[PDB]
Length: 449
Length: 66
Image (cartoon, rainbow over all chains, first blue to last red; front, side, top):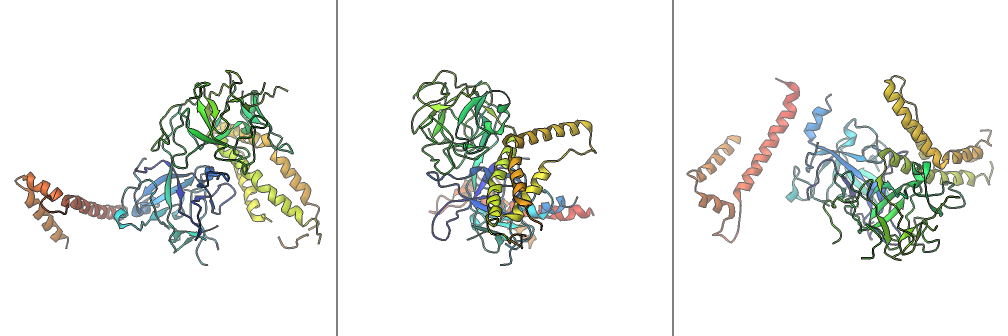
């Protein structure tokens, strides 16, 4: 099928590591992370991948020469040989080459800007059958070529580089224009109780394993958000059905939910999680009754009014609350007619926020233990975490004083919301721990970084 | 020579004038031969590439006006 402008598809390279065998997608997490890397999206078994960061958005497959005049200052079909604008939807740090030493071929990296030659990539397919200036088909191989440094895109075998060597890169489908009232995977949304599904915000020795429906402001909390993954890699984002099987990645900690029939049902680390153990799926009502439907995924379940209950497959057990107010959420056939999951989509900003917060929690820690590691010998992700800091600083600032009051105030509401959101986990206190660990020194240990 | 192309495809037009659709289809599918070809697909393709010339002629000349 044709791949048009304004569509979500990942770049799945056929990246066997010169032997065997993983079909890893291109990925770069976005905020605080200019540098490119690689993530699995094919090991759909005991070691589940990380799909959320791979989701590039198609943008502008304009002609090369056409780009030249736009430099001199909306569903156009994709065609071979055009420069293409691209995106990490999570960050909107558009995919791009950048000038760094990572052997003289500059590494690709995610600049925010829609400016410049950097964010464009002409295609030069090896198949003359598909000459440049031809409509892209689903899954097609291609070698991106920088418009900027004029390097070919490449997989340095792991290391990523824009070199004169030529890796192919498939456009694996995810979603094509989601409609409101029509639920999709790879796409966060709350699991309501009437009040909604969530887990403890302590993020402590209690590894958020506890699982509870809960009302009030917890519903705004990131902890009450869930990134569903349908048991498909292609068209993961295609519209969901009340039946088709699906993975349940957590958003705030990134953990896959899985079949721990102990504690009924509970969160588990994204390592035990299994494609089998996570095989949850929606149902219209408590009932025990083709696949995959690729190419768009038919519209069905509401972002709002409609109920769906999640029957499991590996155990077959229905999800339900077990009984301060902390009603649980556990797997067995009955429970009661009141799981009340009238699903509704998460806001854009909520999700980037959240996923970023998991990125941050996902980054400080090794930094912390690693700085603490030479505290044992008085006498190390430095610059990447500095990048994370200045990124959050950017992410968290006041509206322009030189602005209209309405946008100042709305933007201030965005600020207030975002601050509240990152405060929901209190990782700031982890920062407080950091500061506690640091300024012992007069200047010192390590004597280099 | 672009003039030759002009002349060539005018020639091809002359194959088809008087509207002999049997001949036009036969150009489309070449049934007498075991092989098959649709010429016209290809002239479309020529139109494509010449068009793409036109286009780059635009993206150059448009910035210079005159």
